[PDB]
Length: 152
Ligand code: HEM
Image (cartoon, rainbow, N blue to C red; front, side):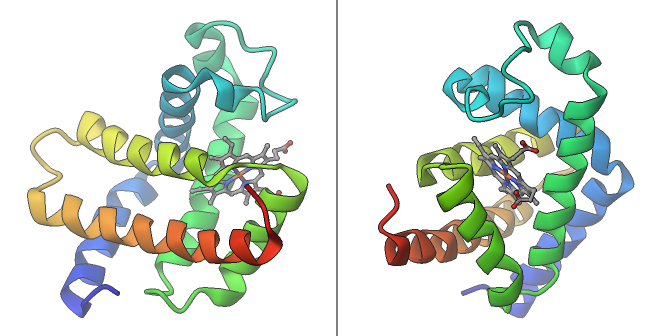
């Protein structure tokens, strides 16, 4: 449950991401994969990436980063009214990709890390609070769908 002012902060922060969705998406995934190498194993199409240099050079990783952040941005712009947008992602990530909710926590924190890394001094405490709450809401609603599906 975010206030109007918190959603305003979220969407203000998101404008930073939308200016360079592929660069943000790439860095989010690289942060996820390098911080939590087990997550790489969930991607048949990225498990060949042995080094961060290879990850950085991967155009397909940037492409997927764009897909991920485009989806997330579409969800965030719903300001919590995202059941229709979230449902297929929860279902695909539980049933097809088999992504534990822990990895969604990892990527949520990776987003925060990337925002500070790319916008140092420009991702204020209020913005971090609002973005964190929005990612918690996202993760929590996914978690509810995971529970429905019995997925761990
Ligand atoms: C912000 C959180 C995430 C968003 C918005 C997101 C979004 C997406 C989207 C839109 C797709 C393609 C459509 C689909 O298959 O449903 C996808 C595919 C996929 N996602 Fe995610 N995802 C997120 C987090 C994760 C995490 C944390 C993992 C694993 C650690 C993961 C693993 C995968 C895999 C393996 C695929 C299939 C990739 C392929 O083979 O093309 N996702 N994701």
